[PDB]
Each structure stands twice: as C-alpha cells, then as structure tokens.
Amino acid sequence: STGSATTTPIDSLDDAYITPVQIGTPAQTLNLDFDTGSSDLWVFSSETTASEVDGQTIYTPSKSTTAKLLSGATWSISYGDGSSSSGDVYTDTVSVGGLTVTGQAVESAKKVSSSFTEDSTIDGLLGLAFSTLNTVSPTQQKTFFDNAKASLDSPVFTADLGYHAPGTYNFGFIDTTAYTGSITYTAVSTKQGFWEWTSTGYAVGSGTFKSTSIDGIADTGTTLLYLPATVVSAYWAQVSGAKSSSSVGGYVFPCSATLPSFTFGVGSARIVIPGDYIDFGPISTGSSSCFGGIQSSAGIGINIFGDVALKAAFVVFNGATTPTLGFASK
View 1 (tube, rainbow, N blue to C red):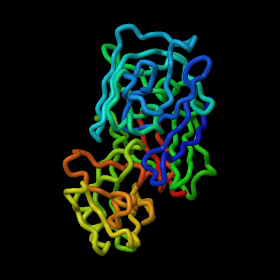
View 2: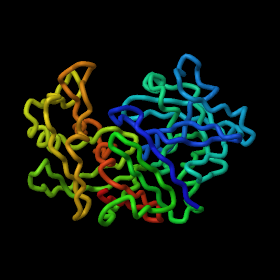
View 3: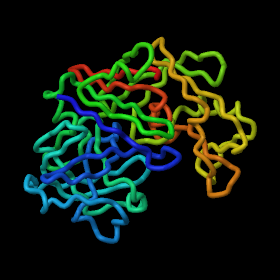
View 4: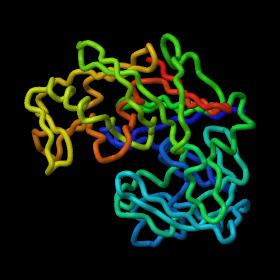
C-alpha cells in the first residue's frame, strides 16, 4: 500500500505545516502537525478541558463506531518549546492520504498548554520519530508509520515541505518526479529515538564550504534551523546589523536586509537554503527588526534540522531494518 497527503503551512511564515488525517468511523478529519521529532499521535477531543479549546476541530470518540478505550492507558508529553499535553488513549482507524491503519493509538487530550490552545489551526500532532519515544503508559504504543510499515510497498515516508506553499508527505514510495538529481543517503542513529544524522559541513552564501561534522535531528515539527553557536555566528556575521538579542530570544536582523543562503552537507552532496527561507519577519507587528531562521542550539543539547532546512530538500525517512535518511535538491 501507499498514501499521499498534501501538507499546508499554517501561516504566512511557514511556522508549521498541517496535514489532514481521517480518524474513526465515520471519518472525523483533523489537521495534524506531522512531527518527525516525536512519537505520539494526539488530538484535541471531546475530553479536552473546554477552556483550553479555542477553534480547533475535536475528535469525539463516542461518535466513532470503531473507537475503543485503551483501558488504563494515559499519556503526557512535553516538547522542546516548553509546551505540553496529556490525556487518555483510544484505538481507532486512522487514514492518511489513502493509507489506513486499524487499531492505531489515538491519544485524546484532557489537557493542553496555552501554546496549543492559542493556535487554532493545529488539531493535534502525528509523531513520526521512533516508537521508543512514545509516552503512553503502562503499555507504550506504536507510531502510525510503525503500524503501517509492513503493509507499505517500501518501508519509507518522504517529506517535501514547501516554502510559502503546500507540499507533500508520501508513505510507502519515493516520487522520482519530486526532486532533481540524485538522493544522497546518510547514516542514522536511533539511540535517542530521533532521526539523528551527521551533516558533513556548511557554507554561508557564496563562501567556501567548511568540512565539519554536525550531529543533529531531522525534525519536521520544529520551525527553525538550530546549529552550534560557532556556525550561527558565522552566518549572521554576513548580515549587516544582525545581532543576538537576549530580550527577543535569538538572532535578529534589519528587515531591510537581503539574507545570504546557507548550505549544509549531506555526505558529498550539498543542500542550499535560499536566504529568503531564513526570514521570519518582524519580531512584533510593525517592527523593523526581523527574526532569524537560523538560531543557536546552545542549551538545547542537540542540533535541529527543522523546517527551514528540510523545506529546501526532498527528504526520505527510510525505515528499513537499519534506518537511513536521504536528501535531494528539488
């Protein structure tokens, strides 16, 4: 089998992407944030504290003839941005772009933190990291991809995120019309539960390529590109007036700037992030100070190849017995 679904930016900055997901019978369609950096499929629901729901579409398990309470199971997750959610668990039928999994754990939120409430466009998350990170207790549950894998034509999914435009998540096949040149594959460590890999270096604008190993995670659920402070300083030093602002919480730059591109290495191959992808707009409405899309990972504890990086590529998440990651230009 295969599936193919369009993923759409939630706003004009590409802060996140939502993908429609069918849950239950009859289908209840929710727009979920596909997150290769976590491993829980959780949704706003009829069980969510009413004051914490503000415009989201909710899953109502009592209206699904295929929903079953997973007795005794609870979940609770905290994300890198300090947000969190928790609740109980149902199993139900879940379909993405025509690909159907029966008995998928659907984690129903009883509580969500303010950042989730405040974002009306995201109805929950669909985790696509390794199932070892799944938070369901006392019986850990599998991701949608893990459950679908054996049925797929090939044990892969691909992320093709757009810049200020829709893109595509495919399951079970590689669309050879969706990228240019060849796909370069690179080794993955699953030891931390992430799609963790090592970039071979970087360049800033038209500058020379610096060969250096940068361990990090491919994370569709993180907006920005988080890299070591040395790398980030080298980038922003090429933008007149750019500075790190402790008050704002990262590098800012004059909105009048033209940003240089940023290149990262995948083996001997190179992915170029155009300068415009690195502009996240005014820090506050009407400001002439703009927020940068490349930020320091210092104090995160890990480098994160988030959407800024991934949307410059066609990315293969190869879930074969030994997982790997592939990157192509597009």
